[PDB]
Image (cartoon, helix red, strand yellow):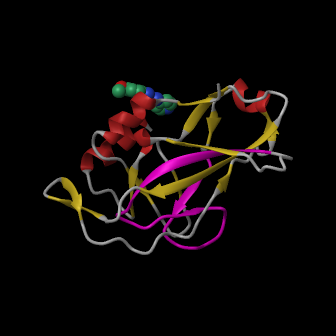
Amino acid sequence: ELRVGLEESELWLRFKELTNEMIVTKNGRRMFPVLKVNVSGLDPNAMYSFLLDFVAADNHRWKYVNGEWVPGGKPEPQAPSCVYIHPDSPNFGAHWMKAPVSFSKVKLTNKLNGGGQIMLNSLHKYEPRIHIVRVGDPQRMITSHCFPETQFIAVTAYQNEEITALKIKYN
Ligand SMILES: COc1ccc(NC(=O)Nc2ccncc2)cc1
């Protein structure tokens, strides 16, 4: 069976229990933690591309009030459908399964300033989602995994000083 497992889930849950935050900027900002997954049950002989996108978790935005994240208004129009193509794409199942698949280079932005960056809206919650696309397939078969442990709010600046401190402590 195809299995995609989250690497460093215990790390992710340390941020998740504070409510996790990722900085978005004009020129784009790498994530911490980095999304990494382990893969078993691909055809080692076949070729596949790895794609990553970020799904809006809620029909509302968030605000940090008295040290607490709370619903903070009605959402902004959905961010334009940005997909990050893993730079190893396309590759053999053997390649993707031999070591963890890391999205270390993905950049999160609040401006449509190109550069393969992902456009997010500040104060909105997103869930990372990975797609495995089989190359040369007339059925264009795609499998999609979501990672609820990796949920975060996009911010132009950190709200929770504990998050600001965790980020320094573990990075
Ligand atoms: C809850 O206690 C934990 C403490 C540490 C981790 N993992 C961790 O820090 N990983 C890491 C890897 C490489 N560079 C920096 C950090 C998980 C749980």
Q: In the rendered view, tell whether residue 157 sits above or below residue 44.
A: below
Q: Quadrant of residue 59?
A: bottom left
Q: Residue at x 57, y 56 (%)?
A: 107
Q: Quadrant of residue 1?
A: top right
Q: Nearer the viewer, residue 36 or 166?
A: 36
Residue 121 placement (x, y as % from top left)? 43, 67
Which quadrant of the picture is home to ligand 1? top left
Q: Residue at x 64, y 55 (%)?
A: 84
Q: Nearer the viewer, residue 103 or 166?
A: 103
Q: Is residue 15 magenta?
A: no
* Farthest front residue in view: 139
Q: Residue at x 54, y 62 (%)?
A: 28
**Residues drawn in magenta:** 105-134
Q: Is residue 115 magenta?
A: yes
Residue 63 placement (x, y as % from top left)? 25, 63
Q: In the rendered view, tell whether residue 130 sits above or below residue 27.
A: above
Horizontal side of residue 129 vs 115, given as left or right: left
Q: Nearer the viewer, residue 87 or 42?
A: 42
Residue 106 placement (x, y as % from top left)? 60, 52
Residue 116 placement (x, y as % from top left)? 66, 62
Q: Quadrant of residue 60?
A: bottom left
Horizontal side of residue 51 vs 75, given as left or right: right
